[PDB]
Each structure stands twice: as C-alpha cells, then as structure tokens.
Length: 77
Image 1 (cartoon, one colour):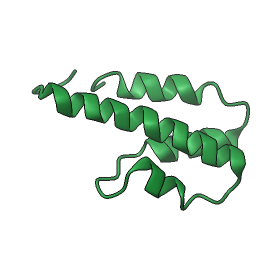
Image 2 (cartoon, helix red, strand yellow):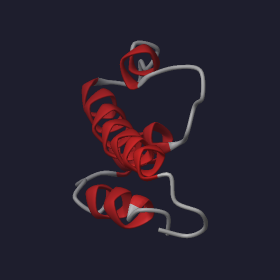
Image 3 (cartoon, one colour):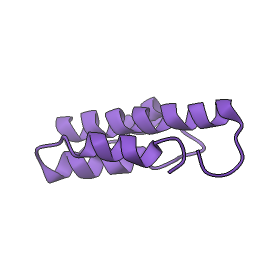
C-alpha cells in the first residue's frame, strides 16, 4: 500500500449495499492527473447513489494522494 490508499478505499467500498455504487466508488478512486473530484463527479450520470459513492471514494483517495505528496517519501508508505 502507499499510505493506506487501498485499505481506506476498500474499507469504504465494503460499506455499500449494492454493486452499482460499489463500482462507482472504485471508479472514483482511480487517479486522474487532470481533474479534481468535483470536476469528475459532474460527469457521472448513472444515478444518485453512484454519484455519492464516486465522490466519497474519489475524496478518500485524493486526500491520501495529497498526504503522500506532502510527505515526500521514497518507496512504499
């Protein structure tokens, strides 16, 4: 893991009652060098729960990537 990135995303994904929002969580967690979470979620249209899960996991993952950047650490965590 990098800074619990996979642990924290998988923790959130395990909370979802249905497969669509779970998948949208994983989609949100994918890194995108060009767009922030708010820009990306604006393009999601499956439905309300997908939107919320996408944004929740995008926020979790990008906060952790921000922490990783802030730490300036070589290698794994």
